[PDB]
Picture 1 (cartoon, each protein chain N blue to C red):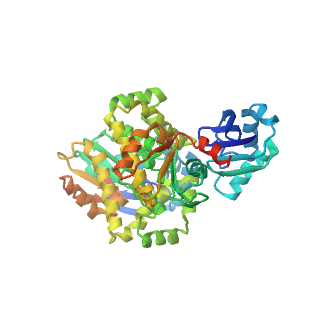
Picture 2: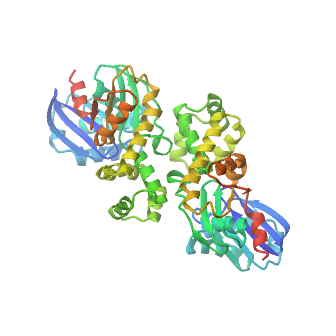
Picture 3: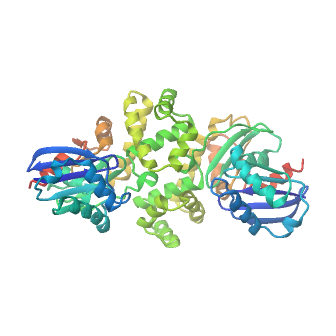
Length: 277
Length: 277
């Protein structure tokens, strides 16, 4: 058996697999070596996974995660995995997870629309080019946080529909003042903004929300996708925003003259296939 | 004599005055009760002002500052002033400073374009209406930080002119990676973004920079100014961004059918007049 894990801001997905056969899947909290020390990662692993995961003969562990983006950060995660499982562990970024999960050994443009957003050209083996996403303030166009940022900007200006404003304040138990406090003074403001992506998804019948999604999705295409040779290679998407707003994403694709026929919630299914070759 | 002080992110201006006559002016660091305790404010005062300020018979002290926006925050500043000067001290916000400095006892729309941005309707006595600015992430349209945010977004995407990108990296001794670090991990990211407003001002001959200013100034008008009865009252501006980019601001005014003939660097001259009545 092998273990394949994919970690983002909201959770880690663990797949215990034999070849392409799923023995078990388990979710734990997100694990990010920029926010968590080696020991916290080890502890979160140790407390989150069932016993069967730790008693099982594993040939390798493939881990992909947000924040696994340098040699040093990959080491922290690797040390935890190696300590917890006593087996070869290979740590890569969430971006390479998207590329390999979406493309296998073919070439094309892989894009993530999740808490943040990301894109790359993948040559079937390595990432060859990677437009900088820029994070929740300076970029991450088309991401959950970008949506949340524009929505909350509109809430404070009273520009959004009253129904949405009232529902937002009630659901989150907030006032305008408390919004400022959360965004400017409390941990992980990006995650709170990105949570708005889930909130807004119930209100898609409103012109306001459709226009907000179209605007942010177009921005991702103009500022990220179209830096690549996007008319000459397949463009494939993964992530919670891409998945939940797949119809609007497809519409934006057609506006830019492309056919987006691959939109997946996560790269996990593709990663299981990839590590079976 | 009285003492009139106006405090923002970059500095405090102190005016020792008899009626409308300026005895002396001194600059110290900014003083903001959200970032500095009463004792730090007192110390910064005590170390920043000349002896003559402390030996002088003063009838009152009028202080206006960023962050002096609640009863409690005003108290902190007041306690410091009262301890340092042993005289009646009246603490108000930087917004009321703009209103009173720009309008005296007349009515109209007062706007600030500085590190952040702000606007209000002033009835000649009190602020009657105040669109929420929203801060550097969710709003502050037309501010230095909004400029810096779009510029740096463009820098990371490689969309800005190469000359600007090279000059930015060299002047600030930064790389793309170090930019992320400053914005996401270091204190007062708003102040660093707002500093870009001064950097860009030397490059106004570039189409890119003109278009950036026009876009951000238009945004301030669409999302803030035009929430007020802006065709029926004078609109007056104060602040470093408004002052440095006065020609483009005036142009944006005309686009929205208004004549902006009052643009001041600071409200200080107006405040001296106001507190002489």
